[PDB]
Image (tube, coloured by chain):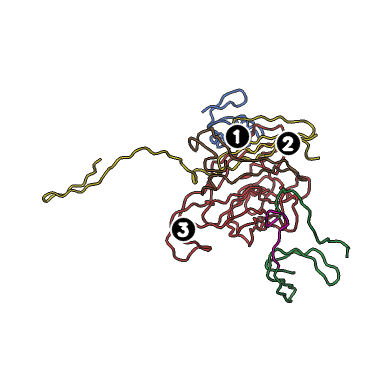
Chain colours: A brown, B red, C green, D blue, E yellow
Amino acid sequence: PGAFGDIQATSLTSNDLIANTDIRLLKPSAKNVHVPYTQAASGFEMWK
Amino acid sequence: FTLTSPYLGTCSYCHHTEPCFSPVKIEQVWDEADDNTIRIQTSAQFGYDQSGAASVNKYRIMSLKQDHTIEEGSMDAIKISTSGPCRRLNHKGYFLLAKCPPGDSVTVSITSCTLARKVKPKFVGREKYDLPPVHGKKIPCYIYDRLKETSAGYITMHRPTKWVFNSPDLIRHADHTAQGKMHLPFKLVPSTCLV
Amino acid sequence: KISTSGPCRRLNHKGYFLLAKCPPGDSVTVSITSCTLARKVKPKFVGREKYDLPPVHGKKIPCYIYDRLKET
Amino acid sequence: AMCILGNMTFPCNQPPTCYSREPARALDILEANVDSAAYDDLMRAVL
Amino acid sequence: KYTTVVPSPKVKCCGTLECSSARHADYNCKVFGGVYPENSQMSEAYVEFSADCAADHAQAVKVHTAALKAGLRIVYGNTTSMLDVY
């Protein structure tokens, strides 16, 4: 994760995505309902 | 096309130093074109004006009172901007399509809210530009098309009546799972532009 | 209406003074129609990571503020 | 091109019923057929 | 790019949640404890493709050894001939 090739897929339309994304969920702390996540950039976005 | 219901959002920095229970909150944003086009996933439905009738000049704001009262705002009054003012182009349900040139903030006013997402400046040629040049040469690019087309993205909606969206603000995913799915408009079709 | 380089929003006033919150720098104007003063307002951040608008969730370290009520 | 509408199967072109005849039962058809491959056909079929 | 499904989370006010994985991509199907004053939230921001990959994606192609065509133009006598030969 971090680099090119986080998501893999044998085509656009098929099933079975295989991901190692460095997504990190974080414990929420606010007055209202949200969901805080952090992540690296997508390795595609950083390869660009 | 407003088969569904609006919602209220929990924004940040609304027209003041105010994160608040908001109107038309951005809630997601796509920045992928090669002009400065932005797609925004707003809080309120935009077609169903008089609580059942999909119209254009009015919309379906879940108003600020905590009673689910939709009050019929005029769609000629939602001013949005990013760091200078920004002319909107299209609206359909939860969605706005505008072209908004600077970055670091994505506002949805009236006065109302914003989002400090980096809208990085991008161009398409090898010689950079800010405004489009006058004469140019037209090499190809992509565009968010603003008439009818859909993207096949398959974002889901659920229960609270009508369908209710799977928003990161919203809560109503407790027992009414196994829910249906719409898909996103504004296909981002290829086109050509001036460099 | 007061402004610095963009439209600035005011908060309070008591006597001569004004308390507003004004983001950018290089000028401070006061309109209705009146003058300006050339004092550069350098932008500042408080943590170890920089930002422009305050973020969404964060961790709330201590800082200093101008209070808005009746204190001298 | 068949669905699993309730317990009775139906073609996805014309499953019963439309958008206005049974609101919140057409939604039950759609939520029962989330993983249907001909799902946009069902979405055109409700309208 | 992922546009992670950031769904509306699952929150029980007094009950508890133990959410495992459905057949999806990367999650972090995480089930945080005492929150929103116990109550519980099981947020699962699972990745998928973006809203549009038919326009902007990539194809990590592997390449083996190659051919050669040509497009030869041969003039003999008073006649020309256009062909193509491996």
**Depth check: D44 or E63 in front?**
E63
* Residue A36 percent coordinates (x, y): 69, 43
**Depth check: D43 or B150 in front?**
B150
Main SS of the magenta segment? loop
Residue at mark 2: chain = E
Residue at mark 3: chain = B
Q: Is residue D14 left or right of residue B174?
A: left
Query: Tags 2 and 3 in contact by the CB under 8 Å rule?
Result: no
Q: Is residue C59 left or right of residue D43?
A: right
**Whether residue B129 is situated above or below residue A14 in the rendered picture:** below
**Whether residue B143 is situated above or below residue A2 in the rendered picture:** below
Query: Tags 1 and 2 in contact by the CB under 8 Å rule?
Result: no
- State the residue position of label 1: D18
* Of labels 1 and 3, the one closer to you: 3
How busy is the neighbourhood of tag 3: few (under 14 within 10 Å), some, or many (20 plus)? some
- State the residue position of label 3: B125
Q: Is residue D6 magenta?
A: no
- State the residue position of label 2: E32
Residue bounds of the magenta highlight: C41-53
Between the C-alphas of marks 1 and 3, the distance is 50 Å
Residue at mark 1: chain = D
Three-letter amino acid code at disc 2? Phe
* Residue B90 percent coordinates (x, y): 58, 53
Between the C-alphas of marks 2 and 3, the distance is 47 Å
